[PDB]
Length: 319
Length: 319
Ligand SMILES: [Mn+2]
Ligand SMILES: [Mn+2]
Ligand SMILES: [Mn+2]
Ligand SMILES: [Mn+2]
Image (cartoon, rainbow over all chains, first blue to last red; front, side, top):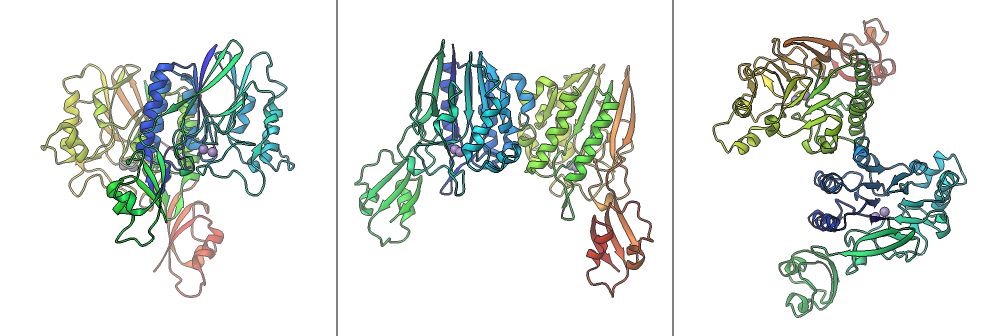
């Protein structure tokens, strides 16, 4: 009878068209920590992609240490944290041996799936992201060529020792077949297929995932993505983002999505140039991050920073 | 009451275009092997752990592994002062979780007013700070020297102190008349960065760092650990290691214990012919060498020919 919070894809330190989202990401984490006080969850899982790069800025590392500190030290919520494809494993893994004392777990090794973490009588199976090279070389299997082959092979390590009488939840970072895609995700593959099938996770009672930034990328009773904390591309402009709440109520699993409201959103406006700089066009919020696809090709003086006096946080201009 | 005194690791240090991390991992390995022998009460690292404020992934992993063996595997308390070279936020990352295993990281110079006491000995922490940073905390224009800011620092703890107790100061600065090395940076912007030994007269002992010669200062109360390795050909032939401090009912005794490196820095003189025919005395052919030779004629690439027989040659000078 526990309450589990499922988030993923923080992508701290991300830059969109030369603009830093750290001012925004600090705001959305303020709201994340604020509503976690009201929930008082039994555990939080962060299903990968915490940093946008393998070389996070001094300011971005501060942000993670501060947010994770409030959640785990002063709110005293246990945390499970796996790595993603963007993540720098060792930069994320730093100091993990001291963190385990206060129930803060970090996993950057797909080998760790054989070692599940048990919180509130629930078994969490962690499987950080791994490429197929580094997967096929641990198993020494040369017939591992697609992401699914290596992922299924990882689960056959743990399938015989798994406990069927408890609640087994898999935390991973991968692409499920049939999920919608945004342009804030990098491809995991070269010319192979990166998607894993639904039947791979038949053993697990539940699957908490991250990689696809759309929260409703996969509609399923057993498998579900958290989605990104914010809109990280204009493909997701306007769509709601946030976190997911999962409650196991005496063997009855229920999941719901809770939206978060950002400091500003991403919006796309099409129309005439003189309609938008003369403010004869409707905009939901003129402080938004904006992509302008406009008319009148000839642009007297600078086209864009004439628009920046009206709309300060404009990012791209297409014509 | 046995204390280990070390400083100036400068992890990630580059010397003449080569990373010294392979050497530093060997000397840190030998340091904790000698920490298994000497069962110590405290290990003190008086600053300058990294070489820049943005260390590489491998350098960060080395500090985590080394510190981990000391604090966790061997259950040794550690105190970490911030030096003039390393970044304060990268050094204190996760310091809140580390205090539960008695691992103390101080990067704030205003932290001197809250000493750490273990085994009946009080440790006052004075991480490095600049006069522009020290000027703003006290809102004083009196302090334009580095010495006055330190005097200002100790005056905070001067009323709040027990002269009865063993009071040790850990800091990172320059003492008057101390010997210099070329791998050290200037601490101020073109003034006098040195401090007289009278400022530290309220303390029973001063453990310092910044000056890489173990015997920079010859004084009973103020001593320098010195750098882990020779980080410049100015330090060629200098013994390096750590200081051991033993206390028994108020009487302090100090020793210097040297670590023998995998490689040394030698400056070799002679002629190209004798040197390449191995008839000039070289301690170890594997050592890092700077050659001042005199055969300025017949050799195609004199460095490559030299590297054939002396692999770790670093610099060549001809006369
Ligand atoms: Mn992602
Ligand atoms: Mn991803
Ligand atoms: Mn220094
Ligand atoms: Mn130094």
